[PDB]
Amino acid sequence: MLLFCPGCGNGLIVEEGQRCHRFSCNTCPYVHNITRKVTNRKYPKLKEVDDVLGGA
Amino acid sequence: DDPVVQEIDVYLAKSLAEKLYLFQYPVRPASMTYDDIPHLSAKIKPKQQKVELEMAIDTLNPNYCRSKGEQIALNVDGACADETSTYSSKLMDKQTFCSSQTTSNTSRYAAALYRQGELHLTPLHGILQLRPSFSYLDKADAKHREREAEQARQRRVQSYEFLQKKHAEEPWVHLHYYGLRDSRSEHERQYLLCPGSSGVENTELVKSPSEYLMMLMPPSQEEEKDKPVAPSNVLSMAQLRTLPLADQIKILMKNVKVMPFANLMSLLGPSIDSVAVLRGIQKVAMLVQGNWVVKSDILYPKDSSSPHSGVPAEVLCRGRDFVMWKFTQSRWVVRKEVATVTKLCAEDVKDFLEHMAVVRINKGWEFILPYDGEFIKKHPDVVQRQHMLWTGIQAKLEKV
Amino acid sequence: GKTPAEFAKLNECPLDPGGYFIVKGVEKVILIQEQLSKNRIIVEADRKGA
Ligand SMILES: [Zn+2]
């Protein structure tokens, strides 16, 4: 997941927010302040069935 | 299935042709626009049209790190010098955008406005992309670096510097910005609504589809490498383009040895002059057993010689003429001895037997096809005229 | 463009393939060469797998 600055179009980066943590642009003063809880979903793959059932 | 629905008319407006320009922001998704943003200055370089903007941005707002704004403001300009200051205030209250030209020819592109029952069209005088300027870092770097701190001929015609001088020769023309919310927009938008009736026959658009095709996709070559007299192998079913008819039959009759005329007009076209081609066929063919046969004298040019890889000999057409005479007098050549009848050898004569005839066992050759209905055409003088020809050639060969 | 009957006068043979050269008196052929195509992108895996 990548996120871009509306101010300058460049990718946004998280920083040590003063009260709440923060996305900030590396160059322009545009900033974004974390309000909500947020996650991204991976869902990795699992082992196949043949040798997981084979032989009990 | 017929054009049964939505038969909307079309209109064209020239009032804004030189004024229309198309601007887009690839970085700006369509879900919001810049209506709320005052553009504080606008500029154009009309010669080699290219555009620059300047606009304001809010600073008090929480998505603005005013501390960062101040810290970088002290850097992009001279910290306390402001020789060429881009922001008199110590905060980034403004931004600027640049533009990029999209094509060298806008003629094939036009703007279109849809209205119920009518479409209005107008060309575009230019299309430029738009870029957010990142140059403030560049001048911060320049500030830090400066704080830290006749003639011979050339082959530099393709220089960057030369085209930048050409670009710099044009000073920047400035404009006053007015947003889409201004009544100015509608006050001018009406100009594209061109006057006119609902529909009138166009002065243009007259050319036919075949004509439209030819000038749409013209020949890449304007002059042909060789003539249609067939200096090289050439089409036969696609009739020769401009060749005179008398020479067209000559071309056709060099291929096939004998041919009844009744199938020709399929090749030269039904519109062929029947009387003229009958006048021309006598020049190249002579009739035997109801069929027009190629003249030897045009089959062998004068300077010919025994072609086949056998006994060399000059252009002795007399013998081939004699076998034609045998076909004329008799029904068919039942006898082999026709070679020695005119004191020729086997190879000398065999090839012309296979020009028209086919073998029967121990009983010689007969034509491949029978006498056809040439008598259906009324010109009995032809058989007599050939008769005088047969008589003359007979008188010659009787000297043997 | 010659005819087989007048090949004999040049001492040449009607069937000879042609298409070769004569240099210093020894007949020589320029063999057809095979090249790989150019200006065409291709992706591949190195010996290391990358
Ligand atoms: Zn940014």
Image (cartoon, rainbow, N blue to C red):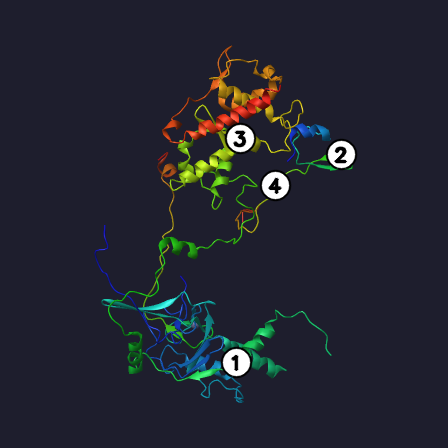
Few, some or many residues within 10 Å of mark 2 (<14, 14–19, 20+): few
Labels 2 and 4 in the same subunit: yes
Q: Residues within 10 Å of mark 4 (few under 14, many from 20)?
A: few
In this picture, residue B343 sits left or right of residue B114: right
Looking at the image, tell me whether mark 2 or mark 4 is earlier in sequence order: 2
Q: Is mark 2 within 8 Å of ligand 1?
A: no
User: Considering only order in the chain, which callout, 3 or 1, is on the residue closer to the N terminus?
Assistant: 1
Dot 2: element = strand
Mark 3: amino acid: Lys
Q: Of circles 4 and 3, which is in front?
A: 3
Residue at the image position 57 percent from the left and 20 percent from the top: B350
Question: On the image, numbered disc 4 is attached to which residue?
Answer: C34
Quadrant containing the N terminus of chain A in the rendered view: bottom left
Gap in Å between the C-alphas at discs 1 and 3? 80 Å
Q: Secondary structure at mark 4?
A: loop
Q: Is residue B235 visible?
A: no
Disc 3: which residue? B295
Identify the mark at residue C26; answer none if there is no mark. 2
Inspect the image, locate mark 1, and give the three-letter code of the amino acid beneath it: Glu
Question: Which residue does the numbered mark 1 point to in the structure image?
Answer: B170
Rendering quadrant holding ligand 1: bottom left
Residue B95: where, in percent of width, then height? 43, 79
What whole-number distance in Å separates the C-alpha atoms at marks 2 and 4? Answer: 25 Å
Q: Is residue C20 left or right of residue B359?
A: right
- Residue type for callout 2: Val
Report the amino acid beneath label 4.
Glu
Q: Secondary structure at mark 3?
A: loop
B207 lies left or right of B281: left
Q: Nearer the viewer, residue B54 or B258?
A: B258
Q: Nearer the viewer, residue B332 or A17?
A: B332
Q: Is the residue marked by circle 1 packed among few (<14), some (14-19), or many (20+) residues within 10 Å?
A: few
